[PDB]
Amino acid sequence: HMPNFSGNWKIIRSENFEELLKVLGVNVMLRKIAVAAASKYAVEIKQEGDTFYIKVSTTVYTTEINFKVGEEFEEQTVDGRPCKSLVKWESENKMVCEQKLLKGEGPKTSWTKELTNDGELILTMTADDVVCTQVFVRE
């Protein structure tokens, strides 16, 4: 197995996190405690070919998703609401994920993950017109 998305990642930048949560209707006090918890974002990925295991965690919370590119799966929005998700590739090293809520009305959300040439992992998370960008390095 050669060098791909696979590995353990630790966050180093986190731009527009608060603003994203606001759009997602999170009250001030929780946004701030959330911004605090985000400087300990760890991501572990196992990638085999087309197929992905991803663990995102902070000090007190973790979640795991499993998916194949091109095949619908379920997870939660950043705000916690369950959703149907679909991942597609965009270049050698970027995937994007459109999301439709299971139940109800809310902002259009989506995320991306990309591996840069300097070997950083870059996560984006979009709610409507607001885009949160997070940068990660190998652990």
Image: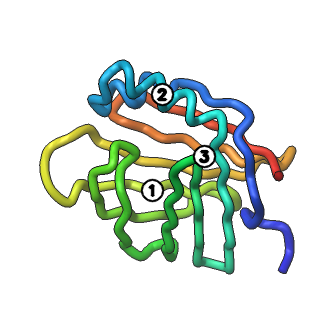
For residue 125, side relative to residue 138 (left or right): left
Q: Position of residue 42 (x, y in %)?
A: 67, 50
The nearer-to-camera label among 1 and 2 is 2
Q: Quadrant of the N terminus?
A: bottom right
> Residue at horizontal 48%, vertical 32%?
34
Q: Amino acid at mark 3?
A: Thr
Asked which quadrant contains residue 7, the reply is bottom right
**How far is the residue under mark 3 from the one under mark 2?**
12 Å
Instruction: Please tell me which of labels 3 and 1 falls first in the chain.
Output: 3
Which residue is tagged 3?
A: 59
Instruction: Please tell me which of labels 3 and 2 falls first in the chain.
Output: 2
Is the Cβ of the residue at disc 3 closer than 8 Å to that at disc 1?
no
**How far is the residue under mark 3 from the one under mark 1?**
26 Å
Which residue is tagged 2?
A: 33
Which residue is tagged 1?
A: 97
Q: Position of residue 53 (x, y in %)?
A: 59, 71
Task: Describe the element under mark 1 as helix, strand or loop.
Answer: strand
The nearer-to-camera label among 3 and 1 is 3
**How far is the residue under mark 1 from the one under mark 2?**
27 Å
> Residue at horizontal 60%, vertical 51%?
113
Mark 1, residues whose alpha carbon is within 10 Å: few (<14), some, or many (≥20)?
A: some
Is the Cβ of the residue at disc 3 closer than 8 Å to that at disc 2?
no
Q: Amino acid at mark 1?
A: Cys
Q: Position of residue 76 (x, y in %)?
A: 35, 56
Q: Nearer the viewer, residue 92 or 108?
A: 108
Q: Position of residue 101 (x, y in %)?
A: 23, 54
Instruction: Please tell me which of labels 1 and 2 falls first in the chain.
Output: 2
